[PDB]
Image: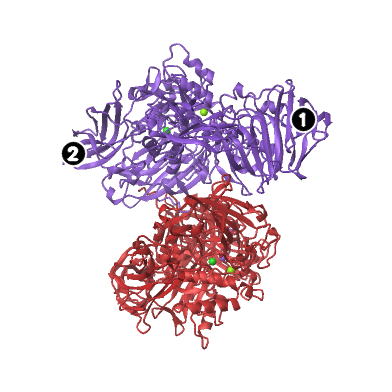
Chain colours: A red, B purple
Amino acid sequence: LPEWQSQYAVGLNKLAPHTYVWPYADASDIGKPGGYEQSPYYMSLNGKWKFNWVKNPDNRPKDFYQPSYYTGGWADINVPGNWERQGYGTAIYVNETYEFDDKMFNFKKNPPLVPFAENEVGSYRRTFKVPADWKGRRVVLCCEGVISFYYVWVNGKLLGYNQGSKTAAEWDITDVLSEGENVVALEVYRWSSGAYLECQDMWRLSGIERDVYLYSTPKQYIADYKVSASLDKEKYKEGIFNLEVTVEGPSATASSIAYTLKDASGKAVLQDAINIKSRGLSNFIAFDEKKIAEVKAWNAEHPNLYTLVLELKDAQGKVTELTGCEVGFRTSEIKDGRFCINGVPVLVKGTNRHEHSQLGRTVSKELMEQDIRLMKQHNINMVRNSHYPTHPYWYQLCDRYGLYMIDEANIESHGMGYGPASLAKDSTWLTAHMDRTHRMYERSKNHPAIVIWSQGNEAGNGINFERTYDWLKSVEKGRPVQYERAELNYNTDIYCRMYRSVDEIKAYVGKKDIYRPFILCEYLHAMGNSCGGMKEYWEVFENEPMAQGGCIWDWVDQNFREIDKDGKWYWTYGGDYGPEGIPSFGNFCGNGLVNAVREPHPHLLEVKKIYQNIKATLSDRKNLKVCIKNWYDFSNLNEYILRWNVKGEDGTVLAEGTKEVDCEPHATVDVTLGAVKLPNTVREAYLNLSWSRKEATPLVDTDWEVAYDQFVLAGNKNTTAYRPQKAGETAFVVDKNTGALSSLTLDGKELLAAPITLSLFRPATDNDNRDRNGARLWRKAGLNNLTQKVVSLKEEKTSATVRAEILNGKGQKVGMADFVYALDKNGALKVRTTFQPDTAIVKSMARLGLTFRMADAYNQVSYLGRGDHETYIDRNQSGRIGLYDTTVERMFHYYATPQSTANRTDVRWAKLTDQAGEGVFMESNRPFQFSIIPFSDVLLEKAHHINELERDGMITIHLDAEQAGVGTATCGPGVLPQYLVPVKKQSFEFTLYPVKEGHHHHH
Amino acid sequence: LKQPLPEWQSQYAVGLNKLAPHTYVWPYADASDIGKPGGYEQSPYYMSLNGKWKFNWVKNPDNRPKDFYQPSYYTGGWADINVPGNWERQGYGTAIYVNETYEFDDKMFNFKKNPPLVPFAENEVGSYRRTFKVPADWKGRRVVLCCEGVISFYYVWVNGKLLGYNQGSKTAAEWDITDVLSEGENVVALEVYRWSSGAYLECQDMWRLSGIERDVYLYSTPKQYIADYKVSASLDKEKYKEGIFNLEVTVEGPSATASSIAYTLKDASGKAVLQDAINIKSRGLSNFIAFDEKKIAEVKAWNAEHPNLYTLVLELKDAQGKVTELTGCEVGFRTSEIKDGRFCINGVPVLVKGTNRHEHSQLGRTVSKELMEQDIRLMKQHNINMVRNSHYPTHPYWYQLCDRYGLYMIDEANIESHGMGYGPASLAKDSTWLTAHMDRTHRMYERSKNHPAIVIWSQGNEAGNGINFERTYDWLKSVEKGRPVQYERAELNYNTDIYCRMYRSVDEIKAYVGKKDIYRPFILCEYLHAMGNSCGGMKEYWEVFENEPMAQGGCIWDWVDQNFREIDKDGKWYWTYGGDYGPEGIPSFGNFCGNGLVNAVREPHPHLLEVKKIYQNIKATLSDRKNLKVCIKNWYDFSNLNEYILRWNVKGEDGTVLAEGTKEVDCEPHATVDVTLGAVKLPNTVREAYLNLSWSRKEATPLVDTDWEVAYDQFVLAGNKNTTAYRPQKAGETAFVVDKNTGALSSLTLDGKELLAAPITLSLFRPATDNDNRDRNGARLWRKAGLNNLTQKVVSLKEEKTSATVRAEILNGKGQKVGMADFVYALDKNGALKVRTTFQPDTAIVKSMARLGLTFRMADAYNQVSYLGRGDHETYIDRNQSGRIGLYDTTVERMFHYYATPQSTANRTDVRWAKLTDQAGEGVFMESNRPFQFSIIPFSDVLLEKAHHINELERDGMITIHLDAEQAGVGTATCGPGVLPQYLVPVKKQSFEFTLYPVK
Ligand SMILES: [Cl-]
Ligand SMILES: [Cl-]
Ligand SMILES: [Mg+2]
Ligand SMILES: [Mg+2]
Ligand code: NA
Ligand code: NA
Ligand code: NA
Ligand code: NA
């Protein structure tokens, strides 16, 4: 059997794992992320390559690696980038299973074997020329990442092969190179034994995923080096620098290796050198430990970096090679049961992140930069490399801009399960587990941003992880090592059990003799309209010293954008490619805080608010005394500016100011703002607090709001100076059969496009579809197919009382409702509703309120209530109560799977008008919720893809006295009890005011 | 109609509020960038707007988002599209390819042509919009929006304010947006229509696409700016040595104080050779400054061979002499005229070795600098000295490249109304379309009037003749005194300074030149149609061009194939053409969009190599074959042969170099020089030897290094006709079997091992090339006679121990009688099998034949091909001046050329012998009694013929062999002359033989 059918054949003739040692000509580029690519000793091989794709190995062009073989008849392929995103094969998205374990491929899972006839082969080949200056030097071929398995040849000679798609494979091709035109070929296989360990919940793709390049060094070169830059454990102020270097290659004469540690300024702070001479082919050099008093420490808030410059020299002292990396002084450890950075316990405010773009697993520098920019802007301080090491550029960015990292080994055998068949318990797979672990470690061991090593993901627990854990502990004395499937067994330094509820977190921290902190590997599943219940999670994290937070599951949605025959775009997910029957797990690949093109979803804004590091509470309402808590770990509040004000419900600034508060990290401080005169013309005022940074960073300028808060101040509950004036004569008609308000006119003009009815359903969010108290129960009760049947109707000159039965499409009695429509002297229509559900049929409701439709011409929306964005009761700490203007089209968020959206909470009043200024003012007798969308609930619920959405000329209005929160049931807890809609007799009202504001012309 | 139809339905609404056509006046900060192609893009006064734009597409204008141009309009829910780039190549609409018709004139769109109207409900609307910020250093300056090219029609808005609209997709449309710009975020929007009245003048034989095709950008100048300027870099008409410099400049905008305009013409080293300055100050917002004529003695002249360029630096200065604006262009001193009935550059009559060129890439009409550089590089490498901008002005960069690398250009106005015809309804005769014609002509001229590479102005293409074209001709004449103006449809009427009638045959060329009172040279606007396996008969064309003073060549039709590359469900790629996109019934003219010398990704077709050989500027003839004295003609117009190196050698048929050397020769342009290489003894072990000549230049060019072969020739030298030293040795015991029914050689064995996968039969057909499918003597007759469905039937058979004689009837699929065949199979003492054949066709049924030879198949394992013959590229009898005879090694796969439409390929001419073996070295050696032709392909003849797309080609494990005693040329019948008489297979009785030697 071929090598790709063996779990043992992880590689052949490759260079031993090591830290990146790119040779530089200019030491100045070492501090520049990706600067090594501009070195004259570096040559990219990215670009166009001849390509051929075939299903079944027996049909492949076997001799294509021979230089003489003709490829001129082949097409070109872009390298890097998965081939499925370039017109070949089929992209498949499955979760806990292996895509090849399906009848479509006539194959059943059976490690280490994978399908033969069904396997796919992508043959890559391109020509290249070595620079003249590389004459006589050593040349190395580096493939940063190729998925699944591949053999590689240079000028017809087989270099070897590789398994392990997320870390680089390298080969010394010096003795195989020729003068002039050279040839490099890779024969890539979609599946291989290694695939059993790459069962991550993500798109299963193929091809060369990352950069392919050449780099040149002298015959004796710097092959690897280990940095240790910590602090003294007593006061965490003195830097402790330790360095070890490995030189390899033959050398008959003497030589030496010297190093210089420079500060950002350029001044050398540490320097040393050792002489070497040996007939052997490798030299291990251990430098004397050095100290730096008052060293500039590295942390997420202040990513101070020193530059390490290594130089290999001749016996004459001439520099033959120069290389290096950035160095950050800090400590990472679990002290007294708590995770601490530089001796300071820190709250982990993170997110998981997969590498994803429209090209597939390939991610550009621009996208990597945008990811980290958005992360910092949204108060995220930690990233977990979602189940595999990332492109080296990512680590460089985190070092530079300050972001903690949980680097992770490319190991996930979810498909084999956690039972006795788990590959974690199969010793024949130790080679594969250890290989991936060694590669993860050696390549990134010197990055200060990495604070935690993760052994892998849901690959089971047993001997293999006990061994890779032991190995990691033997080489790493400055970073905790964790693994979620080890749960509470010895082989994990942090308890990171994923998706546990608040109660389960409390249960853990309240257990006797625990010695490790609880930091969720994954929590708050952000699929679709989600992230509800975040507040409950953080009230615990902020109160329990050994419950330090976690990483939100997924930063960016794994969707691809396609355009249909009518030019309508949509996001794609499982099952959207290939013939019927193709393995699929649907829309579960989109779980991000932002969409595939990095546009934030509304819930990311909730995350920004909950993750902010400056939190205040109102201590004294009359004199406005606030208690500020500084949640930064290494920054004083005086590094930020407080910009406050007080505004009436009408939006006028009643008072304002600017302060600079001094406060130690983790300390609280009181700041009195002073009483404010509230007019009798406002029912309430709002104390607004907004913070920004004095000094800008390259990712966040001085205008960005880093944290904010709001407190509601009571005013004149009796004033009505907000209500609009009478616009004219208002009239209403009641349907004699449904009892619903079928007509509402203003001087004869009809305002309704659909009648006002009782609404109890909501087009299911993805969480609603899995929540124990969600859509399953709403659809079972038939709450989405409601009908009203009058049993009593008493009309009057200006009012009408009615009792009607609420029936589902089955005829069953969902409940009983009473409506009282009365017309006020001001022309305003008050609508009181009293609903009594039949608890024997209705086990849960999505909302309780009224719904109707209007022409889509009424697109101008204005409202007094919570924020500029979408919020729900269990996700509304974010935003601000205030006056907002927008449009219906603007409020609609395009979730991959069309679902409920555009909700606004803590609403006092909402208003909708057309270009001419005509419309309606809507309010209740207490804060309510509302949503206006450009589609019908019917179509929104039915649609599973964006492109199915179609307008019909009407907008849909929902006025809610009650509406459930969203939870995170797609994976983890559903909506908490206190956010579920009560299923009991309830009464509520809404008053509609017709309005005529006129047509205002302006720029 | 209560309301008028929208602007896009009127031939008069060509533009609104746009800048008057002018030469590019990009403001620079670093004069050093003027002489650099595309340099202006690096200026701090230039800001590109290319990139990601919000996009929305709809069929039916009534369905478009009307208020999208308003900044407050929300586009967050829209997708993004790349700008520039036709939208059909970005997943929107339907790419359509039609030739002489309007794609909207079809039942599918419920519309019939009716100028100036285009469909309404079926029209497409592409809504583009993006945000942008203005550079802080642009505060107070004039800012201009420039759209280099958008197709069919579009409205443009900035910050919600309608700037105007435009018709004319191949020249820039600009607007002064200074007054509508605002601090902070600005918004620019374009509402583009697939069809508009202007489309009636954009009926070129090319893909019909939509959207923003070229760069969109902003540039800023001060309030008083350099609006336009006209350069005239000529030479005296008596000696053509003294350069004459003239320059006019137009300055627009206000200015309270005094100002002045100055210029400095610098040579390549940066030294000033001319300079002057004029003062100006007016209450008028427009000032015209014409400088005094200056002269340069022995000025460095510009031409395709030596494109010496000067740099014109213009500076607008304050009252204090402070520069307010810097700009300029490259200057090339030369004259272009029709002198004594002959086209002459700098007083010299030049042969036009050109090609037509459309702008094409996988993104559509949009072409990258990388592709433009490749185009020009390949052109120069293959000895092309002229390029015709195939029916529309190109992107500015193309002209800059031609100025710098030396390539003559025929710029052409974006005017073609082929769909309306040349009759009474021709838009060239409808006076209401004058504005449309004149607007496009003005724009073509103003934008490029200063490029030295442009030597001829063309008014358009296949748009009829009449009042409109006579008017535009007269206009160009009133403004241009240094360039000939031509129009092919004007034929021989007054409005054209050059007779460029397309696709005329050799006789027609001779007939014109021999006509009384002609006063204009004949230079084909288009000729030698290069569609599929084409370009036959090129030699006959150039024998005339080289010997007829007033027949000076022309431009081959199409540089590059207009095909797109797609990938099918099985991962097999293929070239697409008309009808490959959209629903059944979509307008289409099939594979006629691919007529290039190179494929869409610029890979050369075999015929470009013939072009290179015929267009070469150094040609020799063997005058004395004893002392090897050759006569060399220098065809360059401005270069002495001493700028080149001649590497020569004599090689025997066995490939051993018998003599070799290197020589430098002096020879003025158009002159000839004799060179003696000396007698060379030939061993009696070779039947012949070849005198090889190869030239390369002494000094490199950025595009052509010193290793590049710029010209070559070969002469066959007689050797010992009786030697058999070359023959392979007996490898074993040979045996054969003759089929009792067909009389075919059904078995050939070596020591009992079968070598044939299919019997050896008589072959008279060939999978049709695109030309064969239209040739008067092509595949229509071959298929009508059923030559592609032949069966042999023995009527007589007589067998001896080592030989067999048979006579058989050749019947088509309809039992008819194609002819009578006689075969004689005989084995040599050394195991060789001699196959003698005599064919007598029945001229009543066979009116034409593709070839006359044998055919059979072998396992694909036999992939090693070797041969002695005209080698290292595909050739045919009417296309084999290129390449040389010699020993060549290759594989079957390497010989198959992938023509968009699968057709015959891989043929080799002047073959002495061919050999085919497997890796182990086992196979068969093949020869005749005289030079022959052969082809070996990895597909069957049946499938190759049937296949219309490359992905339909499928291997069956067998390769197909063809040994031809005769095979027709390929001609250019797809459009123009079919195969010439002397290259048709004679339809008569003929005998021929082939001998097969099994090898091991
Ligand atoms: Cl890996
Ligand atoms: Cl134009
Ligand atoms: Mg999993
Ligand atoms: Mg035409
Ligand atoms: Na998922
Ligand atoms: Na839905
Ligand atoms: Na054509
Ligand atoms: Na064909």
Nearer the camera: disc 2 or disc 1: 1
On the image, the x and y values in percent for residue B59 come to: 53, 41
Q: Does the residue labelled 2 lie within 8 Å of ligand 2?
A: no
Give the chain of mark 2. Answer: B
* Observer-nearest of B363 and B62: B363
Q: Quadrant of residue A259?
A: bottom left
Badge 2 element: loop
* Observer-nearest of B656 and A994: B656
Q: Quadrant of residue B239?
A: top left
Quadrant showing the N terminus of chain A: bottom right
Q: Point out the tag, 2 or 1, that comes first from the N-terminus.
A: 2
Location of ligand 7 given as a quarter of the image: top right
Badge 1 element: strand
- How many residues crowd mark 2 within 10 Å: few (<14), some (14–19), many (20+)? few
On the image, the x and y values in percent for residue A161 come to: 57, 62
Query: Which disc number belongs to residue A16?
Result: none
Position above or below: A944 against A433: above
- Confirm whether residue A500 shows in the render: no
> At label 2, which amino acid type do we have?
Ala
Position above or below: B753 against A570: above
> At label 1, which amino acid type do we have?
Val
Q: Is mark 1 within 8 Å of ligand 8?
A: no
Verify CB contact (< 8 Å) between mark 2 and mark 1. Answer: no
Judging by the rendered image, the residue that carries numbered circle 2 is: B256
In the rendered structure, the answer to whether residue B334 lies left or right of residue A770 reads: left
Query: Which disc number belongs to residue B824?
Result: 1
